[PDB]
Amino acid sequence: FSCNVDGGSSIGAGTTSVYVNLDPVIQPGQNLVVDLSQHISCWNDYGGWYDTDHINLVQGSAFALQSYKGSLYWNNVTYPFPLTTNTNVLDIGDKTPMPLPLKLYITPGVVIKAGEVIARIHMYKIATLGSGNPRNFTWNIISNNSVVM
Ligand SMILES: CC(=O)N[C@H]1[C@H](Oc2cccc(C(F)(F)F)c2-c2ccc(F)cc2)O[C@H](CO)[C@H](O)[C@@H]1O
Image 1: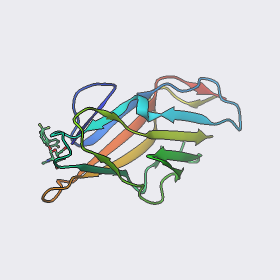
Image 2: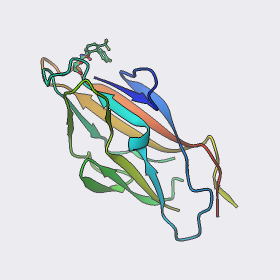
Image 3: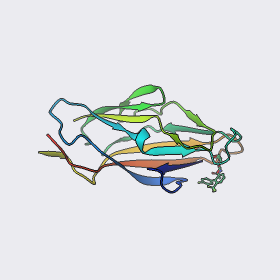
Image 4: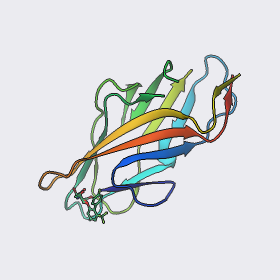
């Protein structure tokens, strides 16, 4: 099982920066949408649904904006964010990269700085054969631009 960010090199585990464009203007009360399907994709390293991968997002995933409320959309369910439970499982068995069905909804001068981590999303992988060779990924979401209020 592997992933990449913006079509880059393969990632098997660990922490990776994910850079996102945010609305530069936000008014008190507005809602920011971060569509991570535009950046993070994952695939099965054998294909053919031979040793299917099972991935979910993990309890504790949170803003970094620590006081913000929000929602996290993952694979047909919208969870309160920060995550207080593990999400449903997405199964990945094709070698073709699958953009992750993942969106973050954020409700808050400069409020978000370019280059600062605004959320840490922990993803867990376990496959089917043997032990499933479980792996941990963390996606550190980073804004490419300032967001001002
Ligand atoms: C030890 C491990 O993880 N076996 C996983 C397996 O891994 C690979 C399969 C082929 C090629 C590679 C490599 F060429 F990339 F090494 C990997 C691999 C190994 C370690 C990683 F950290 C990530 C991918 O692929 C499977 C389907 O996806 C399951 O996931 C399975 O459990």
